[PDB]
Amino acid sequence: EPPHLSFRSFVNALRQDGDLVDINEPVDPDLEAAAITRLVCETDDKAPLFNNVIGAKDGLWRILGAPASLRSSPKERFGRLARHLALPPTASAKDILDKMLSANSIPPIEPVIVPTGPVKENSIEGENIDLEALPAPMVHQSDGGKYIQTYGMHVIQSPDGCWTNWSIARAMVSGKRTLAGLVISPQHIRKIQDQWRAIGQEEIPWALAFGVPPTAIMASSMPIPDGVSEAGYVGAIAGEPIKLVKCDTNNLYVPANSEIVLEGTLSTTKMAPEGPFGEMHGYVYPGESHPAPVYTVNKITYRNNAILPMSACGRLTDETQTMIGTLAAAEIRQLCQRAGLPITDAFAPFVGQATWVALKVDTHRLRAMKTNGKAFAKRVGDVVFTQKVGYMIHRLILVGDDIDVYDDKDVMWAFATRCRPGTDEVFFDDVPGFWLIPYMSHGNAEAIKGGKVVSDALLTAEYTTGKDWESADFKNSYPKSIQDKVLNSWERLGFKK
Amino acid sequence: EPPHLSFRSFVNALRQDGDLVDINEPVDPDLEAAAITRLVCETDDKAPLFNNVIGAKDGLWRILGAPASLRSSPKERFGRLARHLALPPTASAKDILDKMLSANSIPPIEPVIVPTGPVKENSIEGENIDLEALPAPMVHQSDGGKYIQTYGMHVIQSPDGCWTNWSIARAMVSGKRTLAGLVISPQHIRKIQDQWRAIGQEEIPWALAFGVPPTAIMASSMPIPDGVSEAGYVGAIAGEPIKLVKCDTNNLYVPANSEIVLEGTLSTTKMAPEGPFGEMHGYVYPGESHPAPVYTVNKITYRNNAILPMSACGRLTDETQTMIGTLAAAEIRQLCQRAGLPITDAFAPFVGQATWVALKVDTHRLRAMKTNGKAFAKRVGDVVFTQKVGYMIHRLILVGDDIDVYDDKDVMWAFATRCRPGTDEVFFDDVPGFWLIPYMSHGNAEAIKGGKVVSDALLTAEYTTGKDWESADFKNSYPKSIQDKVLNSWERLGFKK
Ligand SMILES: Cc1cc2c3c(c1C)C(C)(C)C[C@@H](O)N3c1c(nc(O)[nH]c1=O)N2C[C@H](O)[C@H](O)[C@H](O)COP(=O)(O)O
Ligand SMILES: Cc1cc2c3c(c1C)C(C)(C)C[C@@H](O)N3c1c(nc(O)[nH]c1=O)N2C[C@H](O)[C@H](O)[C@H](O)COP(=O)(O)O
Ligand SMILES: [K+]
Ligand SMILES: [K+]
Ligand SMILES: [K+]
Ligand SMILES: [K+]
Ligand SMILES: [Mn+2]
Ligand SMILES: [Mn+2]
C-alpha cells in the first residue's frame, strides 16, 4: 500500500526521505520520548521513531513522535505533511490544503470491506487488558495522566447507522480498562454522543485506531461537513477506497492496516477527571483537571511491531499548528466562497498559535461588489464565527492579493501597516468562543463566548479605485532591468547566494 | 580613533569583521546602488561600500549602504549596531539600548573644539555648488527626487544658543543650491524651526553632517529630551568628548572627522515640493509630493575619498526598524519608570514594522498595586501616547516577565494567547497619530489623530495571585535530569547540532 494509505508505508517513506531517526537505544515513555519529540518540533528536526520503548511487551509498542511537524529545509518544509497525501516533499501549504479540500466537489469513494488485515495480527481481550501496564507516554511533566491518545482516530457512528465520524480528540489512561478524554461542543464526536444520549443509550459503541492511513488522520483533523462520513471523503482525496475490517467486539469498522485498535464504549452517563494537558496554545495548568467522558476498552488488536504515534504538542511547531489551524483555515476559505465572499486563499499563520486565520481577497472582485471595509469585516465575521469551522479561530485578518497569506512575514506586515487598530476592526462578543485559549478560560470575560475580531487589513482605496502604492522592496521599487543587473552581479561581487 | 568615534574607522571595523563588500565595479547612483542595498537589507548580508559611483567627481563621493542593518549570523545579528557603540559584535539588542540609555543618568561630557579636521580637506562654495550634478542616489524608483539625506545628522540651534539639536530627517535635492525635507511636529528640528519663525528669522543657521561618529548618528535617531543637546549625551555614551570644528560660513559646530558637511540655512518661509519617499513602513505612494521647507547650501566641505552613507529603507530589515522604533522603545521604558509604572524593559518587535512596542512588566511589583489589566492599560497609554517618544508607536503590548520582549516569537506568542481581542485592549481615538502609516494617511479616519491601542497580554491571575501555568516547551515541561539526558544523547542519536 502506498504511504498515504498505510502508516507503516508512511514511516518507511520518511526513512527513505532521510526525515526519520531510528532510536534503537532504550527510551523511557515517562517524559523522555516526549522531551526528544518536543525538541524535534522546536527545531524542525527529523521525526523520531522510538524502536525500544522501556516497558514495551509482546509488540506494544514503538512510538513515532512528530508525525506531521515541519522539516528544516525551506524547499521541503511541509514534506512530512505531503507524505500523508501522495504529494511531493516540495509541496506548498496551499497544495496540501487544496488537496484536502479536493473531495468537497466530487463524489465520495466509499470504503471497501476486507475480512482481515495486519491490525488483526495480535489481540488482548477483557480482563487481560491493563492500560496502566502499557507504555503510554507522559507527554508533559504537569499532565494529569498518560496521554496514550494524541494522534489516533476515534470512530463513532450515529444511531441510524448512516454517519460514521472519524476525528482526533485527546484522551489519557484513567484506569485498568478506561480512558478519559475531551468530547466538546461543537465537535462531531460530541454531536453523536448527544444523539445517543437523547435515545437513552448509556454506553456507545466506539473504536480508537492508532497509526491509521495518513490521508485518514488528516481528514480526522479536518472539520468536513456535518453528517459526512470521513471514510468516503478520504477515499475521494486518495482516488481509491480505504480498506476497512470489522471490529471483533462491535459492529464498527477500522482501517485494516491500522497499527493498534482499541474497541469499547464511550459513556453518556459517566465522567472522570481529565487533564490538565500541555495543549495547542503552548500552556499547561498544573493541577487543573476537569470532568470528561469515560471510554471503556474491551479489546485491543494490533500489528506485529506496532507503532503508537504521538504529538508532543505545545509551543511552535507541532501537529496542532500544522494541522488544526491550517485545516480549519481551508474550511473557512470554502465557507467564505460558498457565502459569496471574494476569498481566494486562507491560512493559519504560525505566529497566531492556531488562533488566527488570514483571508486573501480577490480585490478586482471586491471592487465589483462596491462595499467598504467596515461593512465587509462585519459580514466576514458573521459568516465565519457562527459556524463550526470558525470555532477555534479568534482573529480573522483580511488582506489584499499582493499579500502571500501562507507567509507569516507578509501577513504581519499587512496587519501592522493596513489595519488601523480599533477603527478597522469589528469585535464579536456574542459568538461561541474557544475556552481552551488562556485569555478565554483564564481571562477577564466569559470563557465560552466572544473574544473574536475581524481585522480589515485592506487599505481604503482597495475597496474603490485600486492599489495606489508601490512596496518599498527589491521586487517592486526597482525596474526589472536593475533587478536583473543586481542578481547577475550578486555572487561575483561577494554577496551570499 | 576608534570605530564608535570615526565613521572612517567604523568602515574599517566592518571590513575587519568580514561585514563589508568593497564594490570596485561601477554602480549607478540612479537606483542600482539602492537596489543592491535593499537586497542586502532583505537578506541580512554584508554592508555594500560603493567605491566607484557613476558620476563621482572631485572626490564626491563613495556610498556606504545598510550602515546599521542586520547580520545573518544569529550570534552577531546586531554586530553592525554594536560597532557604532564600542560594544562587541555579539552584543544583544538589550545591550545596545541599555548603552544608549546609560547617558541620561550621568553628567554630559561636553564636546571639545579643534581648529580643523579631516572634514576641512576639500571644499566647494557658493556659485560653484551644483547639488543636481552630484551623484545623489535615487533610492526607490517612485521617489520624488534624489534622497541625498537618509543617514546624516542635521545640526540646528535654538535662538537662545543653549540647545544644539542633532537629528536624522530625510531630505532630497530640490535645486542647484537647495534641499527639501521633512520638518514635522513633534520633532526637535521643527520645534526649533518654529522658535525661529516666532521671532521673525527668515534663514536659520544649519548644517548637515554625513558620516558622523557612529555614536553621534545613534543619538541623532534617539528621542532624548527637549532642550538636551545631543553632543554632551553622545560624549557620555562614548566615555569622552566628540571633537567639533566650527563651520566656515556660520557659528554651528560639526564633528571634525565627518565625511561631508553641508553648511547653509533652513528657511522659515520658503517651501518646495518634497517626496514621495519609500519609507519605514514599506510603502511609497507614486506622485504624492507635499510642500516641505527649503534648506539652502552655501558651502560643502569634505574628507579626501569622502563616503555618503545611505539607508535604502522599506520592508524589513533596515535602519528605520533597527534604530527608530528601538530607540523610541528605550525612551518609552524610561518614561514609564519616571511615571512609576512597573516596566523593566521595552523593545520594538520587527514584525510591527516600527509601529509596535512591547513593554515588560515586573509582575511582583504589579501584584503589589492590586490593579487590573483594563485600568493598567489605560494608564500606560495615557502616559506614553501624549508624549513625543510615543508619537510613532500605535500599539503597545504589555507582557509579563516570563516573556523576552527582545524576541518577536515570544512577543507574538504572548499577544496571540494572553490578550483577548477588544476585551483586553484600550483604544485611543484622541491622541496624536502618525500620519505616515498607510492606515492613517490613506485610511478610514483622521490622518493625524487616534488609531492607537494598548493590548493587555498579561493573563488575569498575573495582576492578583501570580503565574499559574507552565509553558508546554522543552525548557519548562521536562525536568532538568531529562533535558540533560536528551541534550547529552542528541547528536549521537542523529539529530542536528
Ligand atoms: C491534529 C490534532 C487535532 C486535535 C487535537 C490534537 C491533534 C494533534 C491533540 C494533540 C490531541 C490535542 C487536542 O486538543 N486535540 C483535540 C482536537 N479536537 C478536540 O475536540 N479535542 C482535542 O482534544 N483536535 C482537533 C480536531 O481533530 C478537529 O477539530 C476535527 O475537525 C474534529 O473532527 P470533526 O468533529 O469535525 O469530525
Ligand atoms: C534612523 C532614521 C531616523 C529617521 C529617519 C530615517 C532614518 C534612517 C530615514 C531613512 C531618513 C527615514 C525618515 O523618515 N527619517 C526621519 C526621521 N524623523 C523625522 O522627523 N523625519 C524623517 O524623515 N527619523 C527618526 C528621527 O531621527 C528620530 O525620531 C529622532 O529621535 C529625532 O531627533 P529629535 O527630534 O528627538 O532630536
Ligand atoms: K474530522
Ligand atoms: K484598513
Ligand atoms: K536626536
Ligand atoms: K489579558
Ligand atoms: Mn466529522
Ligand atoms: Mn533632540
Image (cartoon, coloured by chain):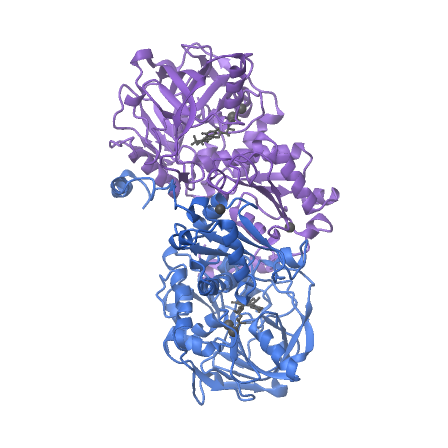
Chain colours: A purple, B blue
In-image side of B483 versus B387 (left or right): left
In the displayed structure, would residue B219 be above or below residue A46?
A: below
Counting from the top left corner in percent of width and height, residue B162 is at 51, 83
For the point 68% across and 66% down, which residue is it?
B289
Q: Is residue A151 visible?
A: no
Quarter of the image where one finds residue B250: bottom right
In the displayed structure, would residue A448 be above or below residue B349?
A: above
For the point 46% across and 46% down, which residue is it?
B413
Quarter of the image where one finds residue B159: bottom right
In the displayed structure, would residue B245 be above or below residue B476?
A: below
How many callouts does the rendering have? Answer: 0
Q: Nearer the viewer, residue B244 or A121?
A: B244
Q: Nearer the viewer, residue A453 or A314?
A: A453
Q: Is residue A248 visible?
A: yes
Position of the C terminus of chain A, as image quadrant, is bottom left
In-image side of B64 versus A298 (left or right): right
Counting from the top left corner in percent of width and height, residue A2 is at 45, 24
Counting from the top left corner in percent of width and height, residue A346 is at 58, 39
Counting from the top left corner in percent of width and height, residue B90 is at 35, 61
For the point 46% across and 74% down, which residue is it?
B216
In-image side of A426 versus A163 (left or right): right
Q: Nearer the viewer, residue B108 or B315?
A: B108
Position of the N terminus of chain A, as image quadrant, is top left
